[PDB]
Image (cartoon, rainbow, N blue to C red; front, side, top):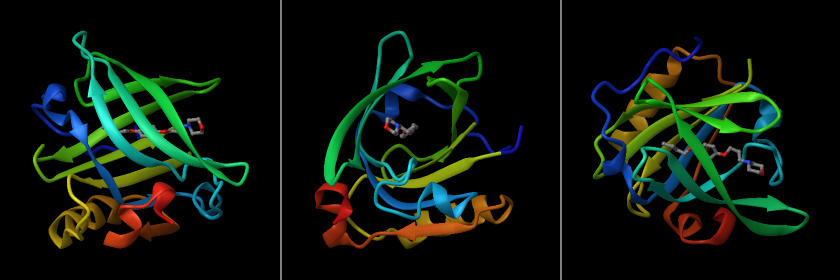
Length: 157
Ligand SMILES: CCCCOc1ccc(OCCCN2CCOCC2)cc1
């Protein structure tokens, strides 16, 4: 109950496939500051299951290397809200998407990280505008964005 933008009418099957973390923001600098920061994660692909859960492939920098991760976000009664199982209850919210170009999401435990996902390794000014508007509300204190060259590299090097 801190992020209160969600996507009405979300069809989670339609988010399947390839995505690029074009921009990210968080409530605390420490959540994204170093390469190995806990929530500096780079999304690779979204794989919605038949039962409506959402499997997520990503990379993360750990121990001086770009590690692959696979995680599962389980559906809830709200179609735009999913839960991930770590030792704390942390939920994922889909704020807005057009399926074909962009998707905005936040994860929250208050600790909060949001990303602007895009389908192609290109700077979508309009997707970034909608991301910044969705965020102007929220209490973000660090924001990163990535150029096309970085978006084609593992962990955005
Ligand atoms: C529409 C769904 C977009 C994908 O949302 C998420 C992307 C990455 C996430 O990762 C959260 C942190 C994952 N852990 C980082 C530390 O290593 C273990 C995995 C969570 C949701």
